[PDB]
Image 1: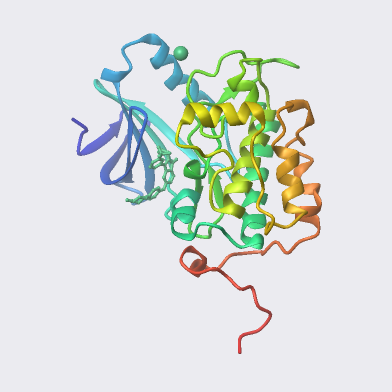
Image 2 (image 1 turned 45 degrees about the vertical axis):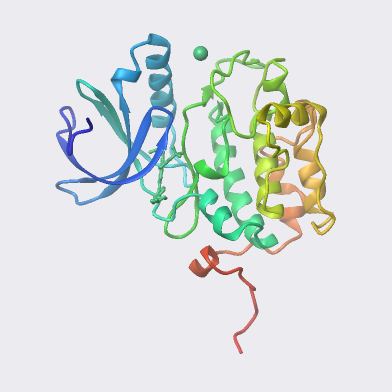
Length: 292
Ligand SMILES: C=CCn1c(=O)c2cnc(Nc3ccc(N4CCN(C)CC4)cc3)nc2n1-c1cccc(C(C)(C)O)n1
Ligand SMILES: [Zn+2]
């Protein structure tokens, strides 16, 4: 049973357990608030009872050690971690506007400048991660959180990995990513190109309003990722569709690096709003010059 109040004995801090946010893996997420500073955060509470096997305990440590080394405007802030007899608690930045998945749920297909707006911040954050030699490996709508200003914050570093040397090919991804890259499925080894693939899939879902490889059978969805079986609707811009085609290639050595993306015609030749109206959560924005 999760405690009503959580206390860290090294930093001397008390966080009051509040609203249930979401359930991921073993973890339960609750909005927690510091007794003294009156600051609210997102709290990831994992039960030790489900961390008895050292393999699962090591995963949690790897996830924390990776997340704590990350400081960026487009990454979910890390404020700490602590533990007790039965639980592991992680203290992270709380984004009150939830995640792009909620936005996708209500809004489905988004306007082209809205996608250009978010994709820029998803890339900027991922650029930071790749500069620090971190592969997220599970980039999806549900872990791209939005703060009050609707700026993207990447979170959920459970499937993340640090690249220890030049040209390293990770042979094992223990876990199941949402936008799983073909090299993961075919077990040929993988590197940074798996994140560009996820970004390509995310781009498709924001512009089209459904995932590129969604089938009833997830195993038949995997067959499609392998065969490169997708079709971009013809109502989608030929510049945006050309970027999706670049990012969704079975050959990882052919996908643009996280650094070349902001320099694609899709970004450089299109309107990228400086900020989005909070109405865009509910209503599609028109982006007009003046109001009649
Ligand atoms: C702490 C675990 C990972 N995580 C974060 O780092 C994070 C940061 N901000 C947020 N914000 C947030 C706020 C509210 C809500 N909900 C409000 C209640 N609704 C019923 C559903 C949506 C939702 C989010 N939420 C955050 N996280 C979060 C919270 C719930 C579920 C999940 C997943 C599904 C990725 O495990 N992640
Ligand atoms: Zn394993």
